[PDB]
Amino acid sequence: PPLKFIVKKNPHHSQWGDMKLYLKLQIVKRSLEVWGSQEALEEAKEVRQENREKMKQ
DNA sequence: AGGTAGTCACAGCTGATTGCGCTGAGGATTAGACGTGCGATAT
Image 1: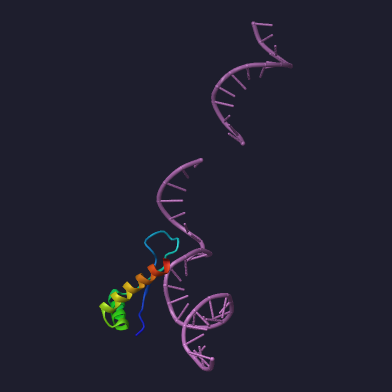
Image 2: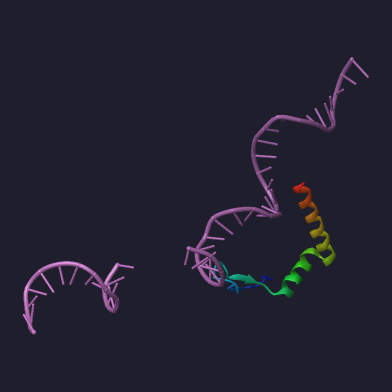
């Protein structure tokens, strides 16, 4: 299902607020569904940072 | 000795990724009292 969000003005200045906020539980559930497991997500972020280091070098 | 498989000079495409434009809030940047001066005027 689509994930809803709340457009809440930032507690800081009125410079550019109106930030979107999502429920943490829904985001975690969606991430687990997409990636299968938390270990897969950890491996994905590790290989992403490794690729970032490879690209910068 | 013959055939072909990479390989490099470009070019194209794709999928991402991350990177700056979108404004807005908390901190450093000359006309009345007071005198004079002068001229018309009390003793």
